[PDB]
Each structure stands twice: as C-alpha cells, then as structure tokens.
Amino acid sequence: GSAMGCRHFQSCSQCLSAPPFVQCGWCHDKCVRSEECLSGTWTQQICL
C-alpha cells in the first residue's frame, strides 16, 4: 500500500499543494525529500 505521500503524487501540483499532509518535495525530477536526494538539493517550488 503506497499513498497519502508527496512522493506518491504523480505531478508537482499536489507535491506543492499539500505540504501539511506530505513531507517530500520535487528534486531535479521526481518528488522526494533530502533522504532521497543524494545531492542534498531539494526544491519545493516549481508549478505556478
């Protein structure tokens, strides 16, 4: 079972539209958090 998570969001709309219910963010491609970004770079702002 995998859901209710920013990393589960297929697009960036919910990734940055539901931050209080998720903890992941967009990282150079897929929506993940530092724990996933091996570069240490994490962006949570891309869609308008």
Image (cartoon, rainbow, N blue to C red):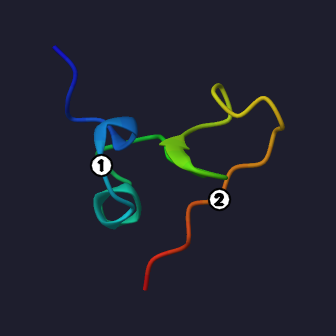
Quadrant location, the N terminus = top left
At 78% across and 48% down in the image, what residue appears? 41
Percent x, y for residue 2?
Answer: 22, 21
**Three-letter amino acid code at disc 2?**
Thr
Percent x, y for residue 37?
Answer: 70, 34
Percent x, y for residue 14?
Answer: 29, 59
Percent x, y for residue 44?
Answer: 56, 61
Is 34 placed left or right of 2 in the picture? right
Q: Relative to residue 41, is residue 18 depicted above or below? A: below
Q: Relative to residue 13, is residue 39 depicted above or below? A: above
Q: Residue furthest right?
A: 39
Dot 1 alpha-carbon crowd within 10 angstroms: few under 14, some 14 to 19, many 20 or more = few
Q: Which residue is mark 1?
A: 10
Is 26 placed left or right of 40 in the picture? left
Say which element carries label 2: loop
On residue 43, the disc is: 2
Is 29 placed left or right of 4 in the picture? right
**Three-letter amino acid code at disc 1?**
Gln
Q: Relative to residue 16, is residue 28 depicted above or below? A: above
Q: CA distance from mark 2 to mark 1?
A: 16 Å
- The answer to which of marks 2 and 1 sits earlier in the sequence is 1
At 67% across and 52% down in the image, what residue appears? 28
Please report contact status of discs 2 and 1: CB closer than 8 Å, yes or no.
no
